[PDB]
Amino acid sequence: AEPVYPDQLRLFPVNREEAQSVKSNIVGMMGQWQISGLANG
Amino acid sequence: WVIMGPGYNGEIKPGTASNTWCYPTNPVTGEIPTLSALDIPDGDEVDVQWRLV
């Protein structure tokens, strides 16, 4: 729904579509075999 | 007049029957309705397309 700038992201709200829109940047910023939730299951 | 089904090749010939096709007394119009416009926040051509899709 809203554009997300990767420099504003913070691993403490994040839709599935928002996570898919910026995917490579989010994947690159997390460790291998790390699992973190987005929203609504 | 009567209408015949498949196997009779849909032939229409004079006849008699008690089961009659009938267009209802007051049929309705099946037009596609028109909805109110959808407003997208202002930006450049690509921003608007991104917000749309």
Image (cartoon, rainbow, N blue to C red):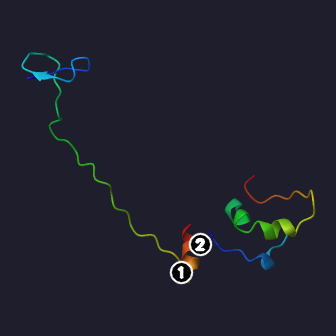
Residue B7 figure quarter: top left
Vertically, is B29 above or below B41? above
Vertically, is B13 above or below A14? above
Q: Position of residue B48 (x, y in %)?
A: 54, 76
Identify which residue is drawn at 91% across, 58% down.
A34
**Which quadrant would the N terminus of chain B be assigned to in this image?**
top left
**Three-letter residue code for mark 2:** Trp
**Residue A13 visible within the image:** no
Horizontal relation, residue B11 to residue A39: left or right: left
Residue B25 figure quarter: top left
Same-subunit check for callouts 1 and 2: yes
Identify which residue is drawn at 14% across, 16% down.
B18
**Three-letter residue code for mark 1:** Glu
Which chain contains the residue that carries disc 1? B
Residue A19 figure quarter: bottom right
Identify which residue is drawn at 18% across, 27% down.
B21
Number of marks drawn: 2
Q: Position of residue A1 (x, y in %)?
A: 62, 68
How many C-alpha atoms fall within 10 Å of the one at disc 2: few (<14), some, or many (≥20)? few
Q: Which residue is mark 1?
A: B45
Distance, label 1 to label 2, CA atoms, is 9 Å
Q: Secondary structure at mark 1?
A: helix
